[PDB]
Amino acid sequence: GSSISHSGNLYTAGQCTWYVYDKVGGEIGSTWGNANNWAAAAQGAGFTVNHTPSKGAILQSSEGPFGHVAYVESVNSDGSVTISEMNYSGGPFSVSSRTISASEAGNYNYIHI
Image (cartoon, rainbow, N blue to C red; front, side, top):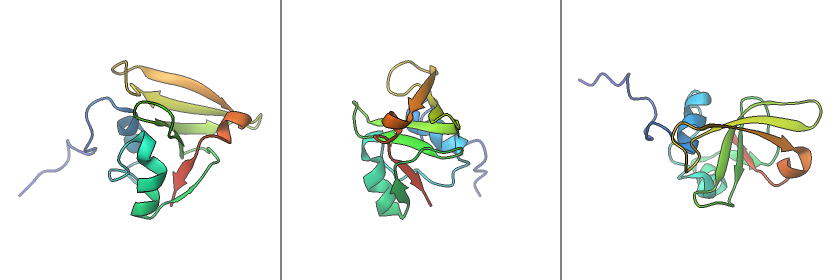
Protein backbone atom coordinates (compact mmCIF):
# COMPACT_ATOMS: atom_id res chain seq x y z
CA GLY A 1 0.00 0.00 0.00
CA SER A 2 1.32 3.38 -1.05
CA SER A 3 -0.32 6.74 -0.42
CA ILE A 4 1.13 8.52 -3.47
CA SER A 5 -0.48 11.89 -2.86
CA HIS A 6 2.11 14.26 -1.44
CA SER A 7 4.46 13.25 -4.21
CA GLY A 8 3.08 14.26 -7.59
CA ASN A 9 6.12 15.48 -9.46
CA LEU A 10 9.18 13.22 -9.57
CA TYR A 11 11.32 16.33 -9.69
CA THR A 12 12.90 18.34 -6.89
CA ALA A 13 11.13 21.20 -5.08
CA GLY A 14 12.04 23.97 -7.46
CA GLN A 15 13.03 23.16 -11.01
CA CYS A 16 12.24 24.66 -14.41
CA THR A 17 10.95 21.28 -15.55
CA TRP A 18 9.32 20.83 -12.14
CA TYR A 19 7.10 23.90 -12.08
CA VAL A 20 6.16 23.29 -15.71
CA TYR A 21 5.06 19.71 -15.01
CA ASP A 22 2.90 20.72 -12.05
CA LYS A 23 1.34 23.59 -14.03
CA VAL A 24 0.25 21.21 -16.80
CA GLY A 25 -1.40 18.90 -14.29
CA GLY A 26 1.05 16.14 -15.13
CA GLU A 27 -0.47 15.59 -18.57
CA ILE A 28 2.92 15.52 -20.26
CA GLY A 29 6.38 15.20 -18.79
CA SER A 30 8.52 13.17 -16.39
CA THR A 31 10.40 11.28 -19.11
CA TRP A 32 11.17 14.41 -21.16
CA GLY A 33 14.58 14.51 -19.50
CA ASN A 34 15.28 18.17 -19.02
CA ALA A 35 14.78 21.42 -20.91
CA ASN A 36 17.59 20.87 -23.44
CA ASN A 37 16.38 17.36 -24.29
CA TRP A 38 12.69 18.23 -24.24
CA ALA A 39 11.75 18.04 -27.91
CA ALA A 40 13.68 14.78 -28.27
CA ALA A 41 12.25 13.07 -25.18
CA ALA A 42 8.82 14.56 -25.79
CA GLN A 43 8.69 13.01 -29.26
CA GLY A 44 10.09 9.80 -27.82
CA ALA A 45 7.29 9.70 -25.25
CA GLY A 46 4.81 10.47 -28.00
CA PHE A 47 4.19 14.22 -27.87
CA THR A 48 3.76 16.41 -30.92
CA VAL A 49 6.32 19.18 -30.72
CA ASN A 50 5.99 22.30 -32.80
CA HIS A 51 7.03 25.79 -31.88
CA THR A 52 4.06 27.96 -31.02
CA PRO A 53 3.61 28.84 -27.30
CA SER A 54 0.01 28.92 -26.10
CA LYS A 55 -2.10 29.09 -22.95
CA GLY A 56 -1.53 25.86 -21.05
CA ALA A 57 1.46 24.76 -23.10
CA ILE A 58 5.19 25.12 -22.48
CA LEU A 59 8.04 27.11 -24.01
CA GLN A 60 11.27 25.26 -24.87
CA SER A 61 14.71 25.65 -26.39
CA SER A 62 17.94 23.66 -26.36
CA GLU A 63 20.04 26.72 -25.55
CA GLY A 64 21.25 26.90 -21.97
CA PRO A 65 23.05 24.76 -19.35
CA PHE A 66 19.97 22.61 -18.83
CA GLY A 67 18.03 24.03 -21.75
CA HIS A 68 15.12 26.47 -21.57
CA VAL A 69 11.58 25.40 -20.70
CA ALA A 70 9.00 27.77 -19.31
CA TYR A 71 5.34 27.00 -18.80
CA VAL A 72 3.10 29.24 -20.87
CA GLU A 73 0.31 30.78 -18.82
CA SER A 74 -1.05 32.59 -21.87
CA VAL A 75 -0.11 33.96 -25.27
CA ASN A 76 -1.18 37.55 -25.81
CA SER A 77 -3.04 38.65 -28.94
CA ASP A 78 -0.21 41.16 -29.40
CA GLY A 79 2.14 38.34 -30.32
CA SER A 80 3.82 38.39 -26.94
CA VAL A 81 3.85 35.29 -24.78
CA THR A 82 3.38 35.28 -21.02
CA ILE A 83 5.40 32.41 -19.56
CA SER A 84 6.43 31.29 -16.09
CA GLU A 85 9.71 29.57 -15.24
CA MET A 86 10.48 28.76 -11.60
CA ASN A 87 14.15 28.49 -10.55
CA TYR A 88 15.18 27.53 -14.08
CA SER A 89 18.66 26.31 -13.17
CA GLY A 90 19.85 29.01 -10.81
CA GLY A 91 17.77 30.89 -8.29
CA PRO A 92 15.73 28.55 -6.05
CA PHE A 93 12.04 29.45 -6.25
CA SER A 94 12.84 32.40 -8.47
CA VAL A 95 9.50 32.49 -10.24
CA SER A 96 11.07 33.99 -13.32
CA SER A 97 8.69 36.09 -15.35
CA ARG A 98 9.44 36.44 -19.03
CA THR A 99 7.70 37.85 -22.09
CA ILE A 100 8.31 36.06 -25.38
CA SER A 101 8.04 38.08 -28.58
CA ALA A 102 6.70 36.27 -31.67
CA SER A 103 10.20 36.34 -33.20
CA GLU A 104 11.55 34.69 -30.05
CA ALA A 105 8.58 32.31 -30.03
CA GLY A 106 9.76 31.14 -33.43
CA ASN A 107 12.88 29.88 -31.66
CA TYR A 108 11.06 28.18 -28.83
CA ASN A 109 9.47 24.79 -29.39
CA TYR A 110 6.43 23.55 -27.51
CA ILE A 111 5.33 20.02 -26.78
CA HIS A 112 1.69 19.04 -26.81
CA ILE A 113 -0.24 15.83 -27.16
